[PDB]
Image 1 (cartoon, rainbow, N blue to C red):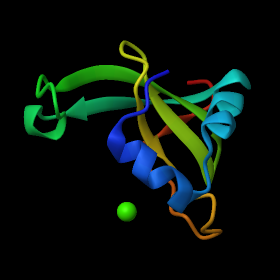
Image 2: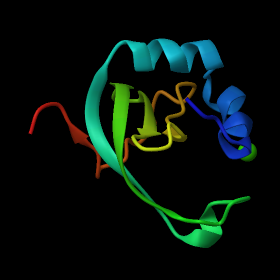
Image 3: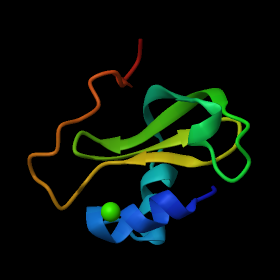
Length: 94
Ligand SMILES: [Ca+2]
């Protein structure tokens, strides 16, 4: 699992400690998404991403991880009961 500066900054704002993220991931995959980032959106490497990603956790309380790199790409705000889940996430079994 890899946590970049962006995610580290969001963690306390969104109610996630590293242990919380690890526990949610260990609970098992709950859906799928993608890590499709343009080159400029991937500092400091600037290589870009076009990889499958897996969702862990539940609606309003989830984390998304790049399947190839292990990078946490998105985390929901668990401190906002009204968090709007990314509608593009494919939950459960297809
Ligand atoms: Ca911020």
